[PDB]
Image 1 (cartoon, helix red, strand yellow):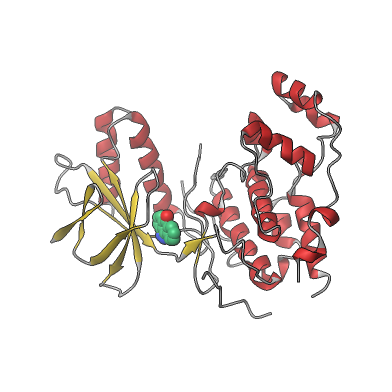
Image 2: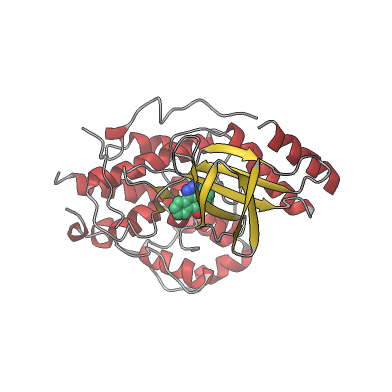
Length: 10
Length: 328
Ligand SMILES: O=C1c2ccccc2-c2n[nH]c3cccc1c23
């Protein structure tokens, strides 16, 4: 399970 | 060697190695700017404590922080980068600056937005990691609010302060009513955030700490009498004078609608149903949480189970603090 390397703050 | 940038109503005299200082820290414990560390080519965070010493309180609140930052170390906790002072000696010594990593923003908004279990359950997983670590270091936060939980674009999560140590909707009953609080105290806070993350809005609002306790019982469920007694004399009355609020189920509280790989959303409910327990004594634990099937996925001993960190007159402080900013 590849850990999420993206997060959308905008 | 140093240079002074006037930020707001106070001059920030930092190392020339830090440019572009910009205030983002309008907190009371200090003013924090966003600089640039030309000697690493990376964004840092500089926080100035103006004369931490000036009264038994501050000098101590400051001495606390300094110490903690030096020995506390985890990827999910605001890491220190550099503490220094422009003052040349203990004599003129009277200003402390802490450089530490710069995160993109707290959870205040990201929570509203819609994030998959992956990003969510994970961000959570990371919080238990710092919290746990913090805990394993005789430190219990208490004041855990998204207002002080910073995140980064790469979906990295960390913790800002140690808060209280020894915006109110994220505190637990043990603090609200004022009572014994254990380590699992910070589990209530996380609980909210997670819910407040799914609900898409403050789980337990309230205009006051009273209307606060009211909406929590109402929503969750009246403390089974055994617990009621644990309450102080006056607060026990209050509760006992209120209608029968058996709350609601976690199914109706957090409907499937709020969620998006099919069981996961109820798997995540099972966790809430163990994190949002008013009776502190039946509330889930960091360990158990990391083991929960909803968080366990991301588990990692190097991170989760980390090795524990480490172990007066006005003038005595100044010397102490200084001694501290001087060990570098
Ligand atoms: O208040 C913030 C803060 C607020 C929003 C985004 C990042 C930070 C941040 N990044 N590093 C530090 C060190 C101390 C305080 C703060 C930071």
